[PDB]
Image (cartoon, rainbow, N blue to C red; front, side, top):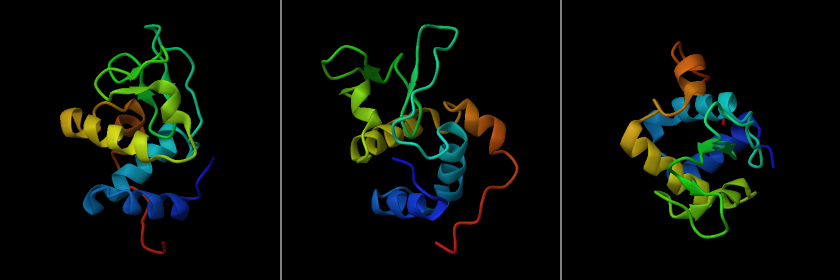
Length: 120
């Protein structure tokens, strides 16, 4: 599925994402997945891939093989669903550790002001 700018802000708030990080989250998502929940990045230098809305790397976060992953305790295929509850708790887990430094999309397209979320 693909959210609109406001459909996404609505979801993130419902999902409990921290309000003052909101514009950063919106920016990140739009530059990592263009708001698609089922997007799957092309292989990086290291055979790793990025999954779903948050483009979460399969190197340390999700399992490629049927049984619940690594640090996020989930399968990467679970981060491609229309319901993003699982991907969210994981995305939060990642932020708690490496902030947004994990996402190159954020480091590149989110360092000079984000979109304004009120209107949503």
